[PDB]
Length: 51
Length: 53
Image (cartoon, rainbow over all chains, first blue to last red; front, side):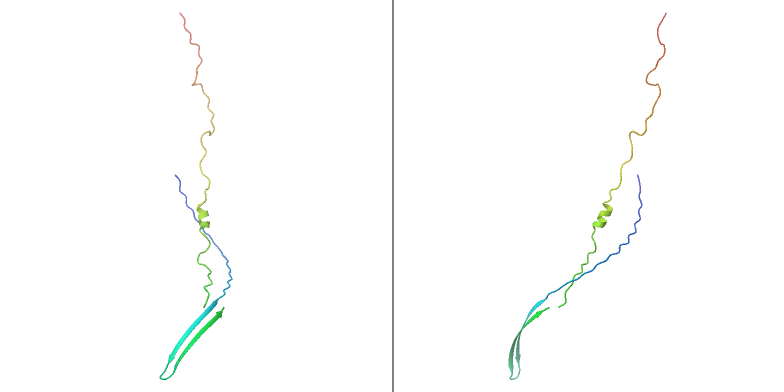
């Protein structure tokens, strides 16, 4: 029979770097109905966002 | 909106720890032949043993 004892100390020094590039499109919509005592309106909107 | 970027959470791989235990090392011990000398006459004898009157 045999017994083994072991100790281990590890020093790990690590580097990392990164880039990233995002390209974002977007198409918005809107409708609106306004009402008053005597004033009524309506509105339609649309939006085109690049990024 | 703001992009996630994603730098990741996982660091390195187990494969280094896996390789650590993966150690095989050296096994078995010397046996059988050893040295072997030996010398004596317990096998056969030699002495005058005849019969007469």
